[PDB]
Length: 99
Length: 99
Ligand SMILES: CC(C)(C)OC(=O)N[C@@H](Cc1ccccc1)[C@H](O)CNC[C@@H](O)[C@H](Cc1ccccc1)NC(=O)OC(C)(C)C
Image (cartoon, rainbow over all chains, first blue to last red; front, side, top):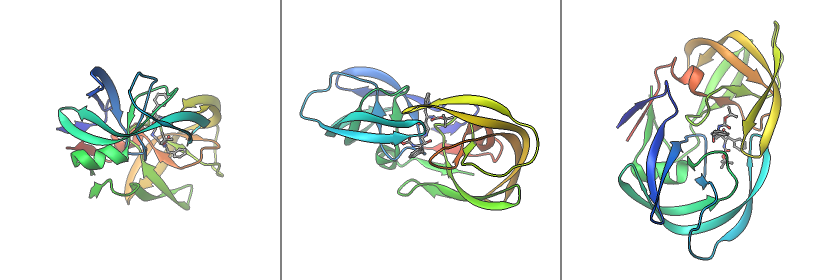
């Protein structure tokens, strides 16, 4: 798809049998999702966004199907105001920014 | 330009006659820059991000040059860790996301 930015770039993802809407975020290095029951061993980690830090659980080699494309990567789960898809997965779908 | 996401999508901007580097951020509704010296009136405003909220000052009608293109918009100035170009200026340079 081609997506213009008059509105938030939101897309449907499927993670761990669950359906979610997430934001295509080119300013996000990492992918971070609201708290969810994701299976496996995760590792605690702190991340910094515009207003300070949040502790997250780091889960590796997780399958995420984004707008239909299957991607595998590291997903952080924590208290975030929004489900963000960052650069670690955007590179996988071959997403480019154009102007 | 075509920009891939293997790296942070950074661009050079000129504002209030100072040269700065900023992130193309599709996940941000707004534009927000580190603490700088800008002329005119402003208004206190709190924004919400990951980690919590920050107090910024809003300036409207501010000229900005993005990767050598002109735009006029609202700019929020605060203690952001990074200079962020959000969807309010991105729609102006005609930027889109492709995948
Ligand atoms: C998630 C993380 C891996 C921590 O990356 C960032 O937070 N990256 C920042 C750049 C940055 C890096 C390091 C430290 C500080 C800032 C971008 O603004 C990320 N895009 C912004 C988007 O995630 C966020 C989505 C959102 C939606 C609803 C509520 C809160 C937040 N919008 C966002 O923060 O927008 C404003 C800047 C306008 C507050």
